Amino acid sequence: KINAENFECLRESKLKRKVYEDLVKEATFVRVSPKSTVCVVTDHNSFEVIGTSSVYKVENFNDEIGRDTALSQALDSFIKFLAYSGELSDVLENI
Amino acid sequence: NAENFECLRESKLKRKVYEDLVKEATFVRVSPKSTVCVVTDHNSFEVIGTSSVYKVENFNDEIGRDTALSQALDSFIKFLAYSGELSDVLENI
Amino acid sequence: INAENFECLRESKLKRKVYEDLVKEATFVRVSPKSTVCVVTDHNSFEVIGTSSVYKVENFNDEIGRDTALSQALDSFIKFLAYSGELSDVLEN
Amino acid sequence: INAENFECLRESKLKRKVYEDLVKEATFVRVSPKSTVCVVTDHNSFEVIGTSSVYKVENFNDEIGRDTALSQALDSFIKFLAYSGELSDVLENI
Ligand SMILES: Nc1nc2c(ncn2[C@@H]2O[C@@H]3COP(=O)(O)O[C@H]4[C@@H](O)[C@H](n5cnc6c(N)ncnc65)O[C@@H]4COP(=O)(O)O[C@H]3[C@H]2O)c(=O)[nH]1
Ligand SMILES: Nc1nc2c(ncn2[C@@H]2O[C@@H]3COP(=O)(O)O[C@H]4[C@@H](O)[C@H](n5cnc6c(N)ncnc65)O[C@@H]4COP(=O)(O)O[C@H]3[C@H]2O)c(=O)[nH]1
Ligand SMILES: Nc1nc2c(ncn2[C@@H]2O[C@@H]3COP(=O)(O)O[C@H]4[C@@H](O)[C@H](n5cnc6c(N)ncnc65)O[C@@H]4COP(=O)(O)O[C@H]3[C@H]2O)c(=O)[nH]1
Ligand SMILES: Nc1nc2c(ncn2[C@@H]2O[C@@H]3COP(=O)(O)O[C@H]4[C@@H](O)[C@H](n5cnc6c(N)ncnc65)O[C@@H]4COP(=O)(O)O[C@H]3[C@H]2O)c(=O)[nH]1
């Protein structure tokens, strides 16, 4: 995973940024189609959390925005898992 | 109550999750076409499943609940895979 | 109700435009102690569902729960507008 | 890819009818040790994504991973077909 300063969703969300730096072990991005980017985030147990993005106009495709949008959805689902285990409370106390 | 749902009678896995790990499963008809199932665990964490019939004139309360519960248990299995408790269910068949 | 009541509509002119012109009805239901369901209806009665779930049940707020569920409901609705091509009509106006 | 290779199409007349009449292309990418991604495109190049993640990575199987991901992708496509009313045309042919 690269530095959190690269992703606009991490700069505007304290919660997502904290989850990204502390609880994300690896983060991979793949362009699977002309319009869609897939982001897979893993925790320390290598559990995979998936997020996707799909640009409406394929001629406006941009790797950075696609990765940032896919990562943002991936962290939305990760926060659901952190709420299930209760470890979300640990993240909230550390902001 | 598990006997009343066809998705549980046909799935040993979802029936085992329902009988042992589901605290409550409530159902609400939220619109002419859609039913919402709210599955909660013993820690009161809520898992939401929905269903929507294509033709509104075909709406059946029982089918809507069974479909939304099956979708809700699909999502709950994801949470069980995250915590590792899914292999406890797969251990007990 | 009127679009100005929702914060996500005041902060997003795309979602406000879709809500004002392409949404027939937007109803909300509290389905559980923590979750709120929003059912968005287009002029052909097709149903788009969005949900929200507050982490701390003692922090439940009706307005925030409705606003969050509506915003996610409009995210899914935009996908349907991109499928039919009506998203291009919204982006022009 | 021919529809006979997918178990989800051999078990669902609805999904197999959608795959052959309304699906232009469906590609598969293994994006991680556990997850497979399927990208279904219609004849207007609109993309519908479906994913599958095996619980035990040692049991990863390419066939099951693709079949599960395609079955998930087609479930989402049916929602788009219900929105445009095009699902009624599929029901005419099954
Ligand atoms: N399943 C599916 N959904 C689609 C498709 N085309 C558009 N959508 C949906 O419409 C929303 C708005 O599209 P937009 O292109 O006008 O704005 C896009 C676009 O402005 C930007 N974006 C995302 N990926 C991008 C990318 N790869 N390049 C440039 N911009 C991108 O993020 C915004 C929202 O991404 P999104 O994936 O969450 O939502 C899409 C997406 O959910 C599609 O072909 N298939
Ligand atoms: N977001 C959204 N999705 C819709 C809508 N209308 C249909 N869909 C989707 O089409 C799929 C197939 O609908 P079907 O009516 O032809 O078969 C339905 C229907 O035969 C049955 N079913 C579900 N709820 C029912 C109900 N309340 N009454 C009777 N039958 C019901 O389960 C099947 C699959 O439900 P589903 O929610 O998983 O998938 C829907 C659903 O995802 C809709 O208005 N909004
Ligand atoms: N399936 C499920 N997901 C949950 C549950 N509890 C939390 N989540 C997830 O974590 C987020 C809650 O964190 P937060 O409560 O601190 O911020 C919440 C909360 O600050 C606010 N919010 C939403 N509904 C609210 C409500 N009814 N009352 C007060 N605040 C609310 O919106 C934010 C994001 O809601 P969300 O639905 O998108 O994401 C949930 C949700 O995806 C849960 O019990 N079940
Ligand atoms: N977001 C996320 N979800 C996960 C992860 N690991 C498991 N899950 C979920 O648990 C469900 C049941 O896993 P299973 O491995 O015991 O059965 C799997 C498995 O028996 C089979 N399957 C799917 N992909 C496979 C594959 N690539 N190889 C072998 N079997 C596969 O399909 C079943 C259901 O797939 P699924 O993706 O819809 O649901 C998963 C999945 O939603 C994970 O790491 N991340």
Image: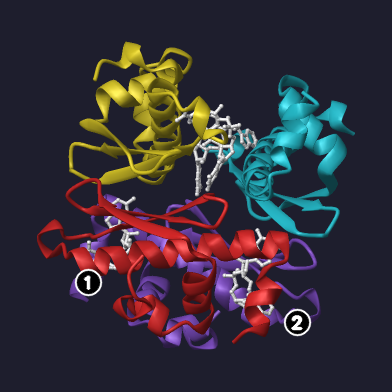
Chain colours: A red, B cyan, C purple, D yellow
Q: Tell me the mark number nearer the camera, choosing from 1 and 2.
A: 2
Q: Amino acid at mark 2?
A: Asn
Q: Chain of mark 1?
A: C
Give the x, y percent position of residue D48.
33, 43
Which residue is drawn at the image coordinates 67% and 36% (left, top)?
Answer: B70
Q: Is residue C85 left or right of residue D9?
A: left
Kindly tell me whether mark 1's CB lies below 8 Å from ligand 1: yes
Q: CA distance from mark 1 to mark 2?
A: 37 Å
Task: Determine which residue is flagged by label 2.
Answer: C59
The quadrant of the rendering that contains the N terminus of chain B is: top right
What residue does disc 1 label? C91
Q: Is residue D85 left or right of residue C90?
A: right
Picture residue at 56% right of the left edge, 74% below the top: C68
Quarter where residue B91 is shown:
top right
User: What kind of element bears circle 1?
Assistant: helix
Nearer to the camera, B36 or D48? D48
Q: Residues within 10 Å of mark 1 (few under 14, many from 20)?
A: few
**What is the number of callouts on the image?**
2
Tell me what residue is drawn at x 15 percent, y 62 percent: A61
Please tell me which residue is depicted at 22% across the width and 68% down the height of the picture: A64
Instruction: Classify C67 as above or below D67.
Output: below
